[PDB]
Length: 142
Figure 1 (cartoon, rainbow, N blue to C red):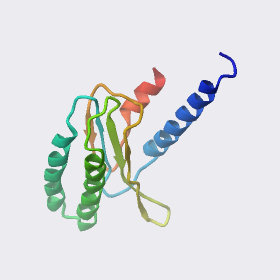
Figure 2 (figure 1 turned 135 degrees about the horizontal axis):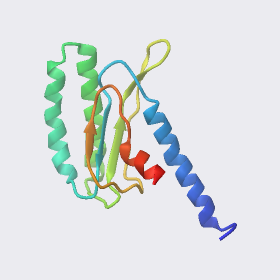
Figure 3 (figure 1 turned 120 degrees about the vertical axis):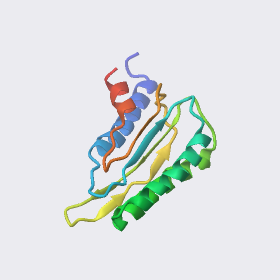
């Protein structure tokens, strides 16, 4: 109404999710290892476990060992969180893992995954050394 408790809870909620977004979009590197996909309430996580397992082959083709190995690490993380919950919630389960190089040129793997309160209506999968949570973006504007 004016100074209710729910109000504050809302601010912190948006502030948190907002932090993960600003970082993601601001997360860029050099080696193709930015695995980011969205699993809405409809796609069986299981189908992803195996689907990702095959993706590993793509790395084998990557001449650049640095990238090949890096790619494997990403798919590995997202694969972990997947089996972790081993469930398909209504809010969905999104994962974000990419390699960002700093000034010195040191890559940073951000292994983060969970089922937030951001239900999507379409699965997405794109990895090209840079990701961008469309769901969170579009959902934010509203």
